[PDB]
Image (cartoon, grey):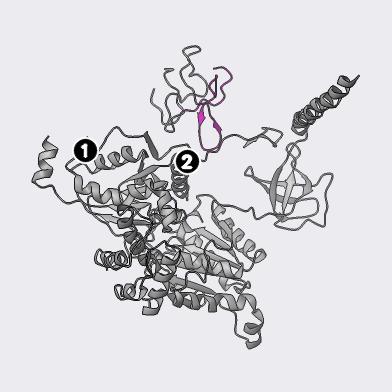
């Protein structure tokens, strides 16, 4: 996956112990901790992966 | 018996302390059911049953009224409160400037003294006479029948301690110092850029006396890039607003605007014409007298062995303003960190002023 | 600060942030380089140490002496000698956080946002202190000319001005350093005349026989 910011626009599933990551001007959801070999994160409002701000979808798809 | 009395006083504390914390968290749920509501500002009142209000969520709506209003705090251009689910005027608010630090950073007074920066004397006096005298005493300008001064320009180096002077004038009047980033007046949305000029002026009138200080004017007062346009129409949109306030029925005399730029060769011709700037202060070469005062002042706060002959130091320059003089001070200090001391000789000071002179003009 | 979705009321406060965090900045906590890795550049080590390193180290000493600290240098003169490499060395030695801030990223075509970026840089730099803000280019906090095209080049006048206004704001305390680097000195607004701005103007010469030989070893 290409992407220039991550944007999972909801995140019900998934410091911190759960992901809620959405990198945008108009709102923000911020979690510092990626990984998540179960559920395998991603899904949601799809652009997902590492961020040009380094919050980061680290390693789902 | 006796022990129960010890513990009775104690466990009544162990309560009282919990109870107050505990009542408060319960108040957070109560507040969560005590909802807020959004603010917009009245564009214009059509009728007492029809208004145009611009909600801050963006679009314009025709609204009527609802319970819990006053109709005598209503006027055009006041902020109002509107319902989330009924979109009608539930209560009427004052209108508010909003204090900011983003697009107008406000510093009541200045953070550096006017008498303490003396040796910058010439500039100090010109600035007093345009600013201080009308602000304290409108009455004298009014009796003659020629208006109080408009707008002042400081031109020549910002790095010689221009900036220091602007803060310093604000300090003595007790004026509200309004520092503006000219680019920040460059929002890319409909009217945000109109809104800022308007807010800045309105607040100046309330919080008058005030200095409105415009940092490097080329971006809100260009000339055009080449006669062409890329983004140099945003510059024109800005610039017409400043000329309009000036030309207007509203008159500058307890709100003073001071423009600053290195060069006068990217000021607009409008501004250079009298009646949008009329006072133009230039930053000069010092006297022999100016240099002495500033050397003495800088070395007074400084720790030194030996009485210093400032008079030699002055000869060793030719027209150093306060910023140039400071580089000479630290230079001396560098051989003193090396000589493992917090003091400096006369001897250091002669060498120091000369090395700084040679490395530039 | 944390506001209810449909009740519009501040329940809680969340940490600070304005735009994305570290958006124009690269963060490298403490370079791996040393002046035992970079060597033969010794004279450029002397200049560099007297302008920035000694005011940082002996900050207290500058306070008691009761002069203010210069916080800044400007370097011009040729790299291709390990200019970048020297900068990182100083960073390692003082135990500064090295922040590579690229001057083209600010220079935004959008309003102000660039101005805010300059302030955020100072803000993090002041929290992380010691810090060197190392500025790739000088062409986009400068090159504004003196003609009537200085109009177009506003974004660049504003990013620079703020960074200086902010340094002299805090000149007595040595926490943050600013270094700009280029091949050669460009047209700029006056700033070489003042301790609290980028006072120091450091030249790179070329090597000599002793220097080439160390560089070869």
Taking the image as shown, residue B194 lies to the left or right of residue B355, namely right
User: In the structure shown, which secondary structural element does the residue marked by tag 2 occupy?
Assistant: helix
Q: Which residue is drawn at 45% across and 59% down?
A: B233
Q: Where is residue C73 in the image (x, y as percent from the top left)?
A: 32, 52
Quarter of the view holding residue B33: top right
In the picture, which quadrant includes the C terminus of chain B? bottom left
Work out whether B136 lies above or below B65.
Answer: below
Residue B310, located in which quarter of the rendered image?
Answer: bottom left
Main SS, magenta residues = loop
Per the rendered image, the range of residues in magenta is: A6-30
- For the N terminus of chain B, the image quarter is top right
Kindly identify which chain the residue marked by label 1 belongs to.
C
Percent position of residue B216, x then y: 43, 62
> Circle 2 is placed at which residue position?
C127
Q: With B160 as the anchor, is B179 left or right in this view?
A: right
Q: Residue furthest bottom?
A: B144
Q: Is residue A24 visible?
A: yes
Is residue A20 highlighted in magenta?
yes
Q: Is residue B245 visible in this depiction of the protein? A: no
Front-most of C55 and A30? C55
Name the secondary structure under disc 1. loop
Residues packed near mark 1 inside 10 Å, few (<14), some (14 to 19) or many (20 plus): some
Residue situated furthest left in the rendering: C209
- Badge number at residue B22: none
Spot the residue most to the top: A38
Q: Residue furthest right?
A: B1
Q: Mark 1 points at which residue?
A: C38
Decide: marks 1, 2 in contact (CB < 8 A)? no
The residue lying at 52 percent from left, 41 percent from top is C18
């Amino acid at each position: 996956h290409p992407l220039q910011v991550a944007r999972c626009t909801k995140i019900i599933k998934g410091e911190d112990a759960k992901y809620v990551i959405n990198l945008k001007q108009i709102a923000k959801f911020v979690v510092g901790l990626g990984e998540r070999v179960s559920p395998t994160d991603i899904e949601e409002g799809m652009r997902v992966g590492v961020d040009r701000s380094k919050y980061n979808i680290e390693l789902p798809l | 018996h006796r022990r129960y009395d010890d513990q009775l006083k104690q466990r009544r504390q162990n309560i009282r302390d919990l109870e107050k914390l505990y009542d408060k968290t319960e108040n957070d749920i109560k507040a969560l059911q005590s909802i807020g509501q959004l603010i917009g500002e009245v564009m214009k009142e059509l009728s007492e049953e029809k208004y145009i209000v611009k909600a801050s969520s963006g679009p314009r709506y025709i609204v009527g009224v609802r319970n819990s209003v006053d109709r005598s705090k209503l006027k055009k251009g006041v902020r109002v409160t509107l319902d989330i689910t009924t979109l009608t005027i539930m209560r009427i608010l004052p209108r508010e400037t909003d204090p900011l630090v983003y697009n107008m950073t406000s510093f009541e007074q200045g953070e550096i003294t006017f008498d303490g920066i003396g040796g910058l004397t010439e500039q100090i006096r010109e600035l007093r006479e345009v600013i201080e005298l009308p602000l304290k005493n409108p009455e004298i300008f009014q009796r003659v029948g020629i208006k109080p001064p408009k707008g002042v320009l400081l031109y020549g180096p910002p790095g010689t301690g221009k900036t220091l002077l602007a803060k310093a004038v604000a300090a003595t009047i007790g004026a509200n110092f309004i520092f503006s980033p000219a680019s920040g007046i460059v929002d890319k949305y409909i009217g945000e850029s109109a809104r800022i000029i308007r807010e800045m002026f309105a607040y100046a009138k309330e919080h008058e006396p005030c200095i409105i200080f415009m940092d490097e004017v080329d971006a809100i007062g260009g000339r055009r890039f080449s006669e062409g346009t890329s983004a140099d129409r945003e510059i024109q949109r800005t610039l017409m607003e400043l000329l309009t306030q000036m030309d207007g029925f509203d008159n500058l005399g307890q709100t003073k605007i001071i423009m600053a730029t290195n060069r006068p060769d990217t000021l607009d011709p409008a501004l250079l014409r009298p009646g949008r700037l009329d006072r133009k202060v230039e930053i000069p070469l010092p006297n022999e007298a100016g240099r002495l005062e500033i050397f003495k002042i800088h070395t007074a706060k400084v720790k030194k062995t030996g009485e210093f002959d400032f008079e030699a130091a002055v000869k060793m320059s030719d027209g150093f303003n306060g910023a140039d003089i400071r580089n000479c001070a630290t230079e001396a200090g560098f051989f003193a960190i090396r000589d493992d001391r917090d003091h400096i000789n006369p001897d250091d000071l002669m060498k120091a002023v000369r090395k700084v002179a040679e490395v530039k003009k | 600060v944390g506001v209810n979705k449909d009740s519009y009321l501040i329940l809680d406060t969340l940490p600070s942030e304005f735009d994305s965090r570290v958006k124009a900045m690269e963060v490298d906590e403490k370079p791996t380089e040393t002046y035992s890795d970079v060597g033969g550049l010794d004279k450029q080590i002397e200049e560099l140490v007297e302008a920035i390193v000694l005011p940082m180290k002996r900050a207290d000493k500058f306070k008691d002496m009761g002069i203010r600290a210069p916080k800044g240098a400007l370097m011009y003169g040729p790299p291709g000698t390990g200019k970048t490499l020297l900068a990182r060395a100083c960073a390692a030695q003082t135990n500064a956080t090295f922040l590579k801030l690229a001057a083209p990223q600010l220079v935004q075509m959008y309003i102000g946002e660039g101005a805010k970026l300059v302030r955020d840089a100072f803000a993090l730099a002041k929290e992380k202190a010691p810090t060197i803000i190392f500025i790739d280019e000088l062409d986009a906090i400068g090159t504004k000319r003196f003609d009537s095209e200085k109009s177009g080049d506003r974004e660049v006048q504003r990013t620079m001005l703020e960074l200086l206004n902010q340094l002299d704001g805090f000149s007595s305390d040595d926490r943050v350093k600013v270094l700009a680097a280029t091949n050669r000195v460009d047209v700029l607004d006056p700033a070489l005349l003042r301790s609290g701005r980028l006072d120091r103007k450091i030249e790179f010469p070329l090597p000599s026989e002793d220097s080439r030989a160390q560089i070869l070893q």
